[PDB]
Length: 272
Length: 272
Image 1: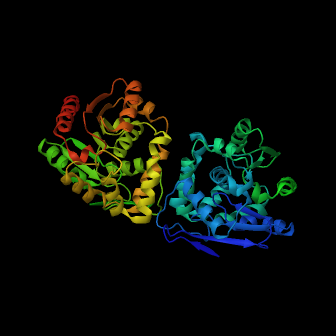
Image 2: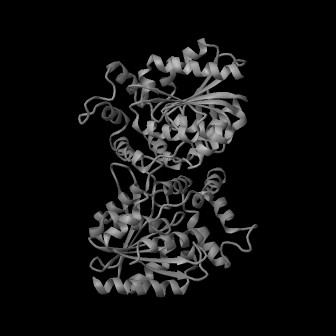
């Protein structure tokens, strides 16, 4: 279904699975992702008795850009706020991958009464260092000049590196499926938006008192570093590292991630 | 005339005034500006024997956005590079107001062989503090929800303040003329782009060895602070303050600004 704003013309594609009386979980995909990345998780979480809400970010798959083609992270938080108001969600847990993790942290900070817990998968509440975002200049250039299918092909092969992004063609092909639904304008805007993350989200997230959980791939050097910094500042956070996983862990779907996830959700649902 | 890129579909509107053999000056307008803001200056500089190049930024007046609706400051530098290559400009002086000043500084840093001098009018090479950009959340919201004509009206009246943005209706009306040619998507994108200024432009500008000049209005608290910080770091810069002028000094056109400007240009042209 679609939630369309008359004021900014963004029409958010979303799905609301499960019974409306069940405990709601909100799934937020990464840059270049969409609800297709969550297929397994929607089925797993429904079988576990949750209501599962997933949506597509501006310019990703079925969601458009609206009146403008640039935005700040705050705009993405406001999109999520509007969706959860539309669905009459009072208290929920948010599961966010990469940018989805950042979004979850800012939402919790801004709406502490609305969130029991956040689960950030290769995400954090921190601003990036400039060096962390340098790579996106070249990915933007490929997206603009050559397009998204070309960009995916470049992401998938590493002539320079001892290995490709995924070892298994099946995972590569799942990534292709998902990534190539992203619009060029949406990819560009999302990557630019990363510069607009406020420097005080860690303080706000600590202030919220919501339960903070993180799952990080040991090979994701950027998010390892940021989440370790985050744990220094939010000692009540629960962090778990997946040895040998990297940024795109949601494509590979290692079993241990789900063992960890369901563990966390058991803690959250105990206290609800 | 237009310079259109086949790779990013940006079609830059520009004007190239004066004789092609004369010393070239490049004029870069602020966010919400366009070549209309430079009318007086084009005439003054032509009468002084310069070749005068002016252009419109992405999404401002006659320039479109291209394939995307978001970009980084680097993208704006690349647009300028393409324009000066198109016009076969080897060595020039750049006069930039506000964002135009920032652009001039990054261009000089990246292309030191191409620039004799930059003149930044309420601009600097520094990144903003977050607090400096907080105001643009509300101006973006007005632009998106109410439009640019409404935004101009809100900028022009200060119920809260001891005075309006301009004391003279004639200056207000000049501002209206100019500002309301800006597209909503262009305003939004430009303001977002401010977050993407690199933190090392001051070092690069100092490295370039180009002559650095700045004119700042004493009432422009943000740019006073940034340019003072810049002068600490680039002691060879020449800074002049206009007492009683503010950010939109290019609308008011005080005579002292031109006395200062022509002075600087005399220094630059002595060494050419």
